[PDB]
Image 1 (spheres, rainbow, N blue to C red):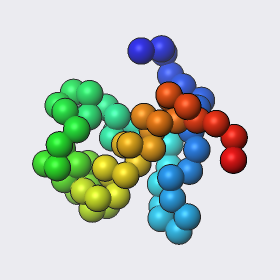
Image 2: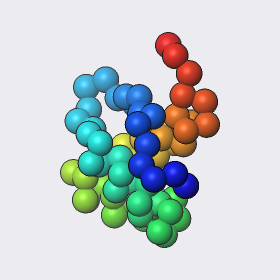
Image 3: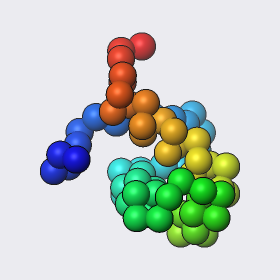
Image 4: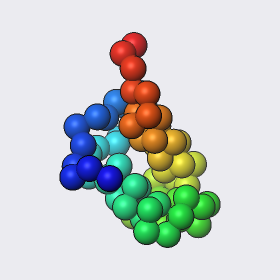
Length: 70
């Protein structure tokens, strides 16, 4: 895992997501494991629901793998 990253697209249209939130998602996901109860911790933390957190987690992964240009 490299020190920091600048590879980040938007996984939302009208929902409030910033650089500080997506860091906490990846932090507790690697610390614990990507489960519904980990997404529920990150939900209460980031003012979201477990669904919102799970979606952005899966975006972040695909951005590090492919990213691309649309």
